[PDB]
Amino acid sequence: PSALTQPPSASGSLGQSVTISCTGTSSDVGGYNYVSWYQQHAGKAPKVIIYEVNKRPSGVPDRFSGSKSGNTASLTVSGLQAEDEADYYCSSYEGSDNFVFGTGTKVTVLGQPKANPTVTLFPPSSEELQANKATLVCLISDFYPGAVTVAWKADGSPVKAGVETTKPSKQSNNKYAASSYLSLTPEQWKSHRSYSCQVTHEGSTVEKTVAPTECS
Amino acid sequence: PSALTQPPSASGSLGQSVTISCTGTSSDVGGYNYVSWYQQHAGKAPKVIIYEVNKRPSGVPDRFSGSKSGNTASLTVSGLQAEDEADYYCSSYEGSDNFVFGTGTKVTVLGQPKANPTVTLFPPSSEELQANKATLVCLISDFYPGAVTVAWKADGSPVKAGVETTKPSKQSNNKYAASSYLSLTPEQWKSHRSYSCQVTHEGSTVEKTVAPTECS
């Protein structure tokens, strides 16, 4: 086990009751009537909340809740409070041994109207190809808040080989921007039908499918 | 709700070695010998690297470790891999099902070489001008260190504005990754002869070019 599923930006105003969740695969989360939550701030000392599936570490405000259903565990920040901007990580368990965390949520308390990505997938430049190089850039810009999820996938099948995802930038109008890239050969690029870039961000999940054409 | 201490930067020399402490109270660390360490990778998920004082996860490497003193507790890092640039937390136990971690230590790996930015200028996709848009992404990857400068030219004299930039992420190496984007309108893309993406980096500059002349 490595990762557990969690949303990118999970947010609202003060009053808004946010909910966050942490799905996995059939035991480890499930059967394991357990998980554990974690409040990251800036630096300020990454603390545990939600002990076992729900009990609190005493000091923690009653209005922090956690609960389970099948393979999904969920945190509820009932009545969002300003100083709640944080990152959230869930853990589980495996033998008298080791354990797994989710791909942490980030709770934004809204300033401005939301924005979910204007993704644009590029193909390789004739240069690149004539250099006998291959690379594809998923330009994910104009969001708020700053947590998007960047999946790539060749001919339907999820892929990894040489992907990267540049974490955010507060682009001059305050909104955000990020990047991601596949690095392949024209071996690799020429032998597939379609390639895509998929960008999740507050429910809205968008996708782009680029095909191989060789110019000439 | 205070710490367990770790110093603020445990600077090593790649190749060599470096250890890192955690100091707690008679209970929290002192008594319950369950201290652990979570290799938080700079913004990411933190994966535990020493559960329960000395016992090593199956998802971690050999040159890693921990030694329980009494109140202090330490990590043993030999053979300084460049991966091991990270922020590390220690954590212990006080009683009543609490766990309590300490600050973090930013272990810095000096000695890793300088790399130069692989500038990759792209042009608008067929399926972009189709919608009457033309953003231009400069890729700037695989460099070291992360002190870069990207400025865009039209063709001749500095053509800024539209340029909304990104701030170099660590890739999956310990090398940087930057994007740039200029946002044209086609009917302002044929009223130019070429386009530039200029990357300055530790003195070595690069300037790369897209001309309108593409199959696209």
Image (cartoon, coloured by chain):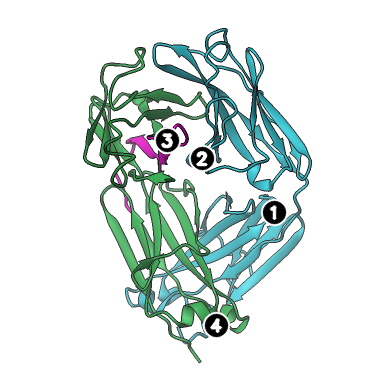
Chain colours: A green, B cyan
Q: Which mark is residue B43?
A: 2
Q: Is residue B190 visible?
A: no
Q: Helix, strand or loop at disc 3?
A: loop
Between the C-alphas of marks 1 and 2, the distance is 19 Å
* Side of B131 relative to A70 (left or right): right
Q: Mark 1 or 3, which is nearer the eye?
A: 3
Q: Which mark is residue B144?
A: 1
* Residue that carries the numbered disc 4 in the rendered image: A126
Hey, what amino acid is under mark 4?
A: Ser
**Where B206 falls versus B176 (above or below)?**
below
Between the C-alphas of marks 3 and 2, the distance is 28 Å
Quick check: is A94 in the magenta stretch? yes
Q: Position of residue A198 (x, y in %)?
A: 35, 61
Front-lying residue, B105 or B167:
B105
Q: Residue at left 34%, top 25%?
A: A82
Hey, what amino acid is under mark 3?
A: Gly
* Residue that carries the numbered disc 3 in the rendered image: A95
Hey, what amino acid is under mark 2?
A: Gly
* Side of B9 relative to A202 (left or right): right
Q: Position of residue A97 (x, y in %)?
A: 47, 34
Between the C-alphas of marks 2 and 4, the distance is 36 Å
